[PDB]
Figure 1 (cartoon, rainbow over the protein chains, first blue to last red):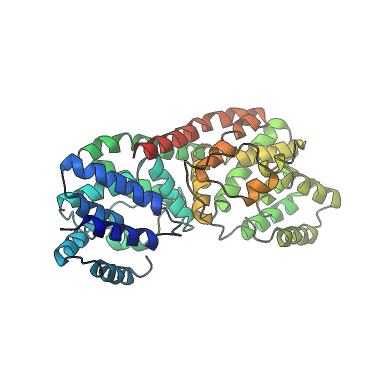
Figure 2: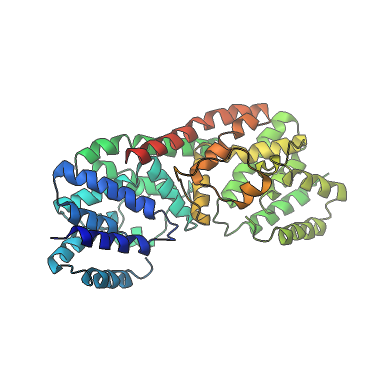
Length: 212
Length: 212
């Protein structure tokens, strides 16, 4: 199983890879998902170090050339007395959690995996979720909204990942669902108060838009 | 004054120069402000064509090279035989209605100016303001929040435009004051159902950040 001084090795690796990010997944996001991952691990008594490990890393991926990403991570993983069993587990979590995959059938997950998916999704919803949502869109010149394009119902991972929608529609395509798919239990009660604000913003948004 | 033909031309000019905006100042923004300027102008009995004209042209001049931009809009107004006095009345507004300016001391405005300003700000608050606000931070790479950094209080022309702040600080530093600064009676009213949302956002954002 992973070790404390290896985790920090992973932490160090994850942060640098994400300095100068400017997309909504920088230190603050990493540390917050990390800080949530931590408390969470306990509420379920899951393997911390493996949990926090995947937590810092899930994102370092997602990236212009996804392949380049993995490799380098495997490399770094290696030069750190990483065990191949501690590695696979990592990619098991980090490679079967992100929403996009749910469009390929709900792939059951590890406990500590479920603890990550939760902590990661918790920081994508709420007021902070709203901010990251649009900040990211503005970092991509993505159409914020268009009363002419409805939110896509049944998508495909390819569409979701390649086809462009509207920042507003993102709430309806994924941001509004993460609270009812939250794995933990403590996460759930935390997802509740974090869903009411997103709606206060979307309805408010469309009301205002329609008024104008 | 400004003729219906020149007006349309200016509209055409504006929308072209703001294509590929990706900062929250593209065609929707322009249209929302426009449509707002028109209602407000009428309620106040303001000269319509000067108003929209100045409304259409405020953002055009976000600009890497402002000089270049100014020296472009004239080429256009000139190509449209807009009269001297009319050209003067257009810069009179645009160039002396921004909040950034107000720092250099209180500057009196026209009625058409107060209307353009109220229209422009009216679209920088409410859910839409929230969206556009952070959507801009994504675009520029600005920081979303930093408990260490607190909202400036005695800003100056430069500080505000040169020295970048945090996204949240912008509500405190600017957006939260607009509705009190609104000029039009019709606007003060409208600016009244557009503050509660921004406040719920900055509040829920700091509640969620600390919680973690």
